[PDB]
Image (cartoon, rainbow, N blue to C red):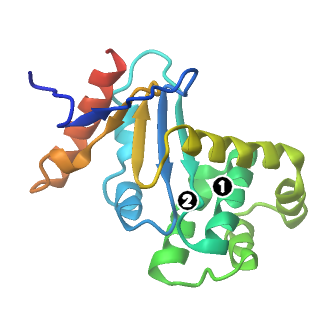
Amino acid sequence: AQYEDGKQYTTLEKPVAGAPQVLEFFSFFCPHCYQFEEVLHISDNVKKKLPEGVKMTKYHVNFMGGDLGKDLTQAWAVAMALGVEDKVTVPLFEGVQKTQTIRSASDIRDVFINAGIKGEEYDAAWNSFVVKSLVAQQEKAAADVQLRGVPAMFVNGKYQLNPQGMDTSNMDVFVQQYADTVKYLSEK
């Protein structure tokens, strides 16, 4: 076939019931994730090729960056609760990997403040039980697929994108192949 299990994707031996339609996992410590966001804009290009009403979910993971990794998963939960993902994603990536100005939870907070989220509003969210459940959700979903690597994308809790098996001489061709694969898996 043109799309083969084990080539542009792999199949989970243990499919995940009730999983989000399109589920992406990343870490702000993850170098290919930085590329996926800043240079390739994967999420957005998948969205553009997805059908009628497909929700896209993106979660942060704990297994990179020790104590700051966990802070970042809580911060992403805040970002999700407040709906400010598109305002903090880039400065968090650059703060962790480019300028290396993020070294504590307080530095993460500074990113939100400078993006215009208010102190009170950040601190209340940070401490809210709604953000706690949201952190739980991120951990659960990663745990449901035994995730030991990022970036990762899962479709309908049954298929996992395999970018290693796609062409990388051309960045744009890579992204389109990636997105076309998500759409193929979507209609599977």
Q: In which quarter of the image is residue 33?
A: bottom left
Q: Residues within 10 Å of mark 2 (few under 14, many from 20)?
A: some
Amino acid type at circle 1 is: Trp
Please report contact status of discs 2 and 1: CB closer than 8 Å, yes or no.
no
Numbered mark located on residue 76 in the image = 1
Q: In which quarter of the image is residue 137?
A: top right
Quadrant, the C terminus: top left
Amino acid type at circle 2 is: Thr
| Label 1 residue SS | helix
Numbered mark located on residue 89 in the image = 2
Question: Residue at 40% of width from left, 53% of height from top?
Answer: 151
Decide: is 131 above or below 46: below
Q: Is residue 100 left or right of residue 85?
A: left
Question: Residue at 48% of width from left, 48% of height from top?
Answer: 147
Q: In this view, does 15 lie to the left or right of 174?
A: right
Decide: is 76 above or below 44: below
